[PDB]
Image: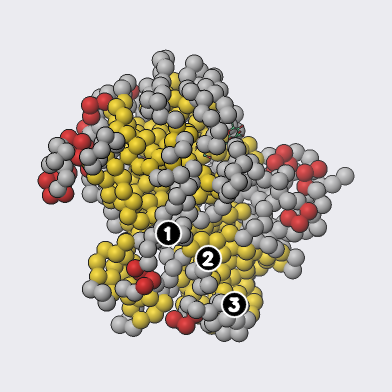
Amino acid sequence: SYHLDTTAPPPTNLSTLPNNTLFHLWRPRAHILPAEGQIGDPCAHYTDPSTGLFHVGFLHDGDGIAGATTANLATYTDTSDNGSFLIQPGGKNDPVAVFDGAVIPVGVNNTPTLLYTSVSFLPIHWSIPYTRGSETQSLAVARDGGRRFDKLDQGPVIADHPFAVDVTAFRAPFVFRSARLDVLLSLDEEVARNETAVQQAVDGWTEKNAPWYVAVSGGVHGVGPAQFLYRQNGGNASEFQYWEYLGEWWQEATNSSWGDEGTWAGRWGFNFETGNVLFLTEEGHDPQTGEVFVTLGTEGSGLPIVPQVSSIHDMLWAAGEVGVGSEQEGAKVEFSPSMAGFLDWGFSAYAAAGKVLPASSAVSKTSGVEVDRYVSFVWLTGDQYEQADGFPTAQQGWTGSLLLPRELKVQTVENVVDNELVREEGVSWVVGESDNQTATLRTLGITIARETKAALLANGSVTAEEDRTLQTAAVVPFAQSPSSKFFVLTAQLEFPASARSSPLQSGFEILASELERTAIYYQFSNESLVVDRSQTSAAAPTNPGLDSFTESGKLRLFDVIENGQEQVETLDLTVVVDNAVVEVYANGRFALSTWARSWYDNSTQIRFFHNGEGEVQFRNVSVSEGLYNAWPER
Ligand SMILES: OC[C@H]1O[C@@](CO)(OC[C@@]2(OC[C@@]3(O[C@H]4O[C@H](CO)[C@@H](O)[C@H](O)[C@H]4O)O[C@H](CO)[C@@H](O)[C@@H]3O)O[C@H](CO)[C@@H](O)[C@@H]2O)[C@@H](O)[C@@H]1O
């Protein structure tokens, strides 16, 4: 008989092992996931007005939305056992399934109200004909603190997609408020043209009584992906039954992309999924003074297309401005991207679902945060969106996980030499100011939620490494490596201006022993942070289910003036390893997550890495081991 021994070689076929045998092998301890089973898209988050607690939601086992709550954003508690479900299919509006949805804190009966996609027909896919009535948007109300959502005893409040529009997908309603949208809509078509008159109205805007907007994601057959915008009828904040259609406030031509070569923001693909609408400043979230930001997943494919197969799942973001609808008979308001990028460059990262976290929340009160924040939760599919080549699912007993909660805001990059590196077309940043000599850049800021980061390094063991410089090729083991696979690695890599043209590759090797290693390094050839997983798992060679393809993201290191002197901006790294869940963060303006399913208990070594091409200076290298338990009650 075979009992799991991770100090010994892995069996050739993991899929032959007994159920639940691999349950803990690759399981994270500081991440959001159900007690067992599979987790899908994150949805339905809301900061309970009454208790100030923050509720988190996610599709679970493809049988509905499950929930959990937190008071500090560090630890979570399941709403209930047996799946901890909030709402499941089988109603009159959702006889087949319950898809993503979002919550209005003070809705029907003045309680948290869920607006979600109720499904009545399958299959549903952008590459095939759409069955009329497949997806409708229904309402459900929170009961018993929010441990359950009861569907309203009536049909959907948005019972059909736009009239006679051949949509590719009509789902994932996301609710939000906006001063600019209210102003542009409450104005005149001629008076809402001059930003002056407009801006003057936004100043007196009052959030408390503003109407809600709903953004539904999808696209149109033969046209392109799009976001369908609605709002409480007539701008009536008390109107929850009728939702007026404002049109396709954002659409792109089929498989087109941001930029001439789709370099910084993947492609718009064939269908938009899970549109989140944000309003960011330089400190957090503000629906009155914040710039419009939209995060979304796009479904793509190579040609020839294989019906019912989305080969590419990009987790994108875009920022821009909202204006009136021109002079055409189309959308009443329109979103125009000025810049776009990736919220996470991970192949398996997708469906980021976020929510405003008020400073008045119990979470922010405890941590002492004085501003409103926007926390986003990204999905890390466990099996490559179910296209994996025989992953040992029954053996693991669970599938997928959410990534660490992330704060999103406008991040600025100061003292940037205004050169070609900054003026390139179709990038993920805009210039905030400049004298043609140095400029301030503006882009999406991405950082681990502060309380979560604090919890990750509150009881961790700290081991630093001496600053180091590598010129010739070398792989240097740390003075002391962690003895577990639960740690946070931080480091700063400084490169010479001369490395830009070089074939330089510099980083670290982690989760390493003689038979295994995972490499993380910066590459100038394509200005990308890369995660080489070719040798990650000693079990991958005979178990194709464990993907081992290379992961990478674009990260441009600008020329800056740090000390009255020019230099290539410092690569500020933060790698969080929560067993197999690996999250690479950089300069607060970059995230790449993936699975690193190493097998041996001894694969915990960490080494400096340099390919000899060019030179690199490592500074402030440190390792915090341990992380923490995100689910105390389990
Ligand atoms: O879960 C619905 C939400 O998922 C999003 C974001 O990922 O897009 C999903 C999509 O692919 C899901 C998939 O299956 C899921 O639902 C099945 C039941 O419908 C369930 O059996 C699967 O176990 C579960 O993973 O759809 C097909 C099923 O044929 C499969 O290839 C997928 O992996 O769901 C839509 C419809 O099935 C597809 O158009 C889309 O790719 C978000 O947009 C949805 O709200």
Q: Amino acid at mark 2?
A: Leu
Going 17% across and 35% down the picture, which residue do you hit? 186
The residue singled out by tag 3 in the image is 610
Q: Amino acid at mark 3?
A: His
Which callout, 3 or 1, points to the residue nearer the camera?
A: 1
Is residue 107 visible in this depiction of the protein? yes
Counting other residues with Cα less than 10 Å from the Cα at mark 3, is it few (<14), some (14-19), or many (20 or more)? many
Please state which of residues 424 and 159 is positioned toward the viewer in this rendering.
424
Q: Secondary structure at mark 3?
A: strand
Q: Which mark is residue 260?
A: 1
Q: Return the disc, 3 or 1, that comes first in the chain's sequence.
A: 1
Please state which of residues 593 and 201 is positioned toward the viewer in this rendering.
201
Q: Secondary structure at mark 1?
A: loop
Going 31% across and 69% down the picture, which residue do you hit? 414
Query: Given contact means CB atoms under 8 Å apart, are the residues at marks 1 and 2 in contact?
Result: no
The residue singled out by tag 2 in the image is 529
Q: Return the disc, 1 or 2, that comes first in the chain's sequence.
A: 1
Q: Secondary structure at mark 2?
A: strand
